[PDB]
Figure: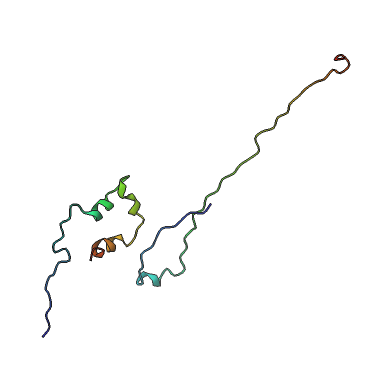
Length: 50
Length: 50
């Protein structure tokens, strides 16, 4: 009597214009440099939208 | 002057071998010295000024 979803995707209807994580990764003097010292950004950026 | 420090990610697995690790506070210093020594000189001939 249990219903479980298989291979569900967190980004179901999400249309990503750009990869913010990738942009933060490759940012040498860019405007994303304010997030470089952040440690758990690689965990916040994935589940911060709900 | 003393500055801010970076954030470290929580890791209990490696928190067992580096409990007594060290991390310097990252301070800075400046020095100032004495650099002006001057004088003003004047003369007065009162007897010949009469």
